Amino acid sequence: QVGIPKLEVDHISFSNVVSMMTANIRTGDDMAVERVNPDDVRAINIRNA
Amino acid sequence: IPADELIDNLHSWMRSVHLLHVRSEDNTLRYNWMLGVYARSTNYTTPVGQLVVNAPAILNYSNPQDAFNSVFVALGIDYID
Amino acid sequence: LKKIAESFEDPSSIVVVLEFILFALFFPTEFNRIKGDIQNVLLLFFSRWY
Amino acid sequence: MLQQPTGGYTTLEQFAFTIRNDGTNATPTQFLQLLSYEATENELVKKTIPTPETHLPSARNVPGNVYIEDAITQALFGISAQNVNAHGYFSRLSALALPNTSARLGLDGVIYNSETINIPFYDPAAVANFAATYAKLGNASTPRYRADMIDIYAHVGLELAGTDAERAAGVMPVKRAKFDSWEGSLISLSRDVVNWKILAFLIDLCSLEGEALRAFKTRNRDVFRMMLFIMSTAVAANVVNRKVTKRVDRVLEYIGVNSMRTAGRTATITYDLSRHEFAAKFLQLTFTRWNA
Amino acid sequence: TVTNEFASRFRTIVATLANVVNERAVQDDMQKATRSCTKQWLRHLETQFD
Amino acid sequence: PVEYGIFVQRGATYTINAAGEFEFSGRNEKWDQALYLSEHFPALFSDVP
């Protein structure tokens, strides 16, 4: 049998498995990059599909 | 419009066009008239245009489909409007 | 490779091409490790020049 | 290593697929009994499915053990999954495709890079037979190998809603599925089905042959139909409820027609474009296997 | 005793590259100028390598 | 403006084919003195009517 989902039914369950990220995973940190400008503005292609 | 003025003008214009190309000896080839005309139309500013300038040969083709595929791959584009 | 942003519009861009060729001569081994990352750049050079 | 029975792995009670319903663990068949239909003027006609590409995408050098069951089931039925192809680890299945590979596909649905202790796994022959087809999920996204996202759904319709007569004919009216329902029914169904160990169903689908395979298809038609159901709700253009004298009937219009919708909605799981491509590919493969 | 095969290889490389730049079509006038200049630059390189 | 339209549409420059006819570039483009050593000639000076 699969188990009954805890939200399917009205009993309160006080032990639960909460997934949680470890130190290795991180989110929302500002991220660094090497932005690099076009060599000449006249050469830039606005147009093509 | 008088036929003489019509003919003289239209002849003058027709003579005015000069589509970029490179003549070759192979008997299988044809010019991709649409794209070269289009590149003329935008004075070769559009990327397909400057393709047509630096590689006129790209317009010549044997398999009809690859005539465009060569342009889509050379330019990386998903389409041309 | 320390990635290079080169459009290869002007002729002078050939510098980058030589920059790889010399790299392949002076350092064939290291070149062999980073060569695919080189190919990503050379492909722009080819699509634009040939 | 778990031995495969003369029937598939599915004969084992350990792999039973059941959606929760009416306070029990209903088998998919007893849920499909609640399904009911309203044919519209429009018609579905099943075109022949294109043969899947021979090409098996490379299982690129990956140090880790990919959780492939979780990846497929979430790609197909998961509530929040997105961009399923950019990580593209489905390719990894091809690692199992080789004869005498060191990789094993555990019952956890993990593709271990090597055999490992206390981790039971499917017989490598059978997993080779399965991977030989389903590694092509890996090339779901490559432009050369994308599957049709439109016509394939007709088959889904025919396999779900389709009466034995319509299935014989190969054409059925576009139907409008409906069932009496509890709140959030489609979501709970999509999770109960996301939890399934579907790799059993697939490995048996791909390794069995002859009378064993035929018995497998008859035994599991409702399982396949249920996966088809969650998927059909992911593509259905809308899902209304109807009042019906102190009961509420959930109503998906329409079965067998991909609306290509990518906008989220509370009623059901949604396919981002990548999920649409992946599912179309999965349907291509599974239906190609379902007919032999 | 006089010939050095490395330098000779770079002669063929740079000669190839110069005939490459020479064949390269350009639109702007400035590009035409840089195209002529890179050839001289290449020649300088080749002597530097020798 | 109009005579210029016609003229530069014929080509900013020209080369001389082995047959000795002038063949014009059919393209607008500024001259640079680099070209002076090339096979190219400014087209104003062609004296081709």
Image (tube, coloured by chain):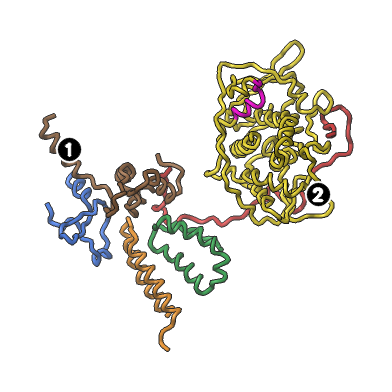
Chain colours: A red, B brown, C green, D yellow, E orange, F blue
The quadrant where residue D158 appears = top right
Instruction: Name the spot of residue D168 as percent of width and height, x first.
Output: 61, 23
Instruction: Mark 2: give few (<14), some (14-19) or many (20+) Cα within 10 Å.
Output: some
Compare residues C10 and B72 and report the one nearer the observer.
Answer: B72
In terms of depth relative to the viewer, which is nearer, B15 or F34? B15
* Vertical relation: B44 (above or below) D193: below
Please give left or right for residue D175 compared with residue D179 in the image: left
Residue shown at the point (78%, 33%) measured from the top left: D17
Q: To which quarter of the image does residue F17 belong?
A: bottom left
Q: Is residue D73 magenta?
A: no
Residue D161 included in the magenta stretch of the image: yes
Task: Give the extent of the magenta segment.
Answer: D153-164
* Vertical relation: D222 (above or below) F21: above
Outermost front residue: D211
Residue located 47% across and 69% down the image: C21
- Disc 2 residue type (three-letter): Met
Same chain assignment for discs 2 and 1? no
Residue D250 shown left or right of residue B65 in the figure: right
Q: Which mark is residue D119?
A: none
Q: Look at the magenta stretch and give its main secondary structure.
A: helix
- Disc 2 vs disc 1: which is toward the camera? 2
Label 1 Cα crowd, 10 Å radius (few <14 / some 14-19 / many 20+): few
* Viewport quadrant of the N terminus of chain B: top left
State the CA–CA distance, disc 2 to disc 1. Answer: 84 Å
Residue D73 visible within the image: no
| Location of residue D100 in the rendering, given as x and y in whole percent from the top left corner | 71, 55
Q: Identify the subunit bearing mark 2.
A: D
Q: Position of residue D128 (x, y in %)?
A: 69, 48
- Find disc 1 in the rendering and name its residue: B10
Is A12 located above or below residue D112 in the figure?
above
Marker disc for residue D1: 2
Q: Quadrant of the C terminus of chain B?
A: top left
